[PDB]
Amino acid sequence: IKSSNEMASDLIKQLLEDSELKNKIFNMEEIKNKIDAENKGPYQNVFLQEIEYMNALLSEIVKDLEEIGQGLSGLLTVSENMEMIIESIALSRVPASWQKLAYPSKRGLQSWLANLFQRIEQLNIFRDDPYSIPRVVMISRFFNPQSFLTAIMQVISRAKAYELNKLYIQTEITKRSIEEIEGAAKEGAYVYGFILEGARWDYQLGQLEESKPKEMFSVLPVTYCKAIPLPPEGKEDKSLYQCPVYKTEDRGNTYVFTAQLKTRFPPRKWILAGVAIIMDVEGVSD
Amino acid sequence: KLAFSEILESVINEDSESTIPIFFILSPGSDPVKEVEKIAKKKRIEPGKNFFNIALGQGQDEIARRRIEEGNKEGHWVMLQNIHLMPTWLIELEKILDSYSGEAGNSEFRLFLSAEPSTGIPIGILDRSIKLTNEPPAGLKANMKRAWTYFSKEEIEDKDPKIKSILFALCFFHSTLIERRRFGPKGWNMS
Image (cartoon, rainbow over all chains, first blue to last red; front, side, top):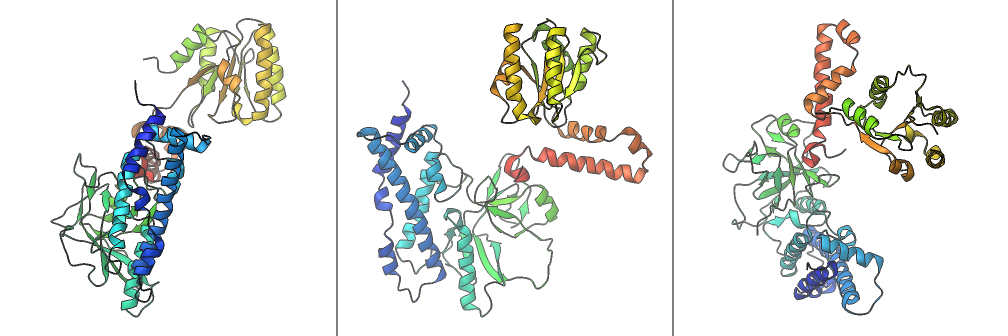
């Protein structure tokens, strides 16, 4: 006597209506009015774009959930795409309609929802005091993390009188945890949520090293993503290895940007070992 | 323990009498025609005149139609290959085999047919048939061994010690690309 597909949805419906989703929906006008629009920096614009994408996702899941919840209990014509959402919810796959909105990350439905609330909770600490940016940003939990990396270069193009184009993003990996308080020191935004697969970052040495036999993913500590001008000529550095970051474990056309991290070994070693950073692994604490 | 030649020998002999055509689903780097010709020669004395290893190409579809028609009433088996190449003629072939199931028409006739695994093969032909995959052994060694085997002994022996050394390294390079595929993201990133 195992719970039917249409019961398994009603349960997830109740968990998502016991959680204040319709409240979690952002109100664009209220947040825009809190911003003066004279002192509005680049960061502010990127978040406002993120909460719009989120508010467009969060509306879509609440609508498709209250529509199937209405269609389950109450008398209503059962749409073809609604049965497809019920079926997918029984399997514990994320639905196709929901997946198309927001981030491309591959998680189980209960993990997806738990991650979605950490996305919301990164924006619920923006809403309160927008002008004051969080000291350590969580690049893991954006929609376009790429759009946030343009933003950090924008802030340095105001401070220093040279072209935004000529800046590339440099990634210094820090020995400090999220304990540290010195918030957004000149030239960079501190960052967390980078997860290195294929190798192991040593903390004490501060260098890329060989992966521990059983431990598959070594989570990187806080990353002081600097902006700095490009080199004059095409130069190759042995010390640094140019590891690409990807939004998901899949690593297929989810390339955000190339990072640079210290290696005593030859770089050729690491490109062959398939070394890359990743945002979402399902090895993210709490 | 049965390798492949002994499997095909067993499944041709024990079953596949007639009306049940013997299907060969093949992967790149596989030849069904050599194995069937060997097994064909042990059971019956075949000079490749009694039985025909007809290759399906545009225009030769009408010759295959005459060969399969001649085969039934005579009692000699017709090997077709690269079946997938004509999707139109397979809907025509299905209609011929349906006619010969009720007719039933010399015994000790067979239809060996070999296709590449593709969509747009008719259901009716695949259903009735005895299907048999001969997949080549996967592995760095088995894939490096196949890389040499490919190059004609006579060509490489003649070539000087320098060039055959750099060919050996290139065979391994070609092998280690195919063997990387196996690991999903951490491997290639693209098929």
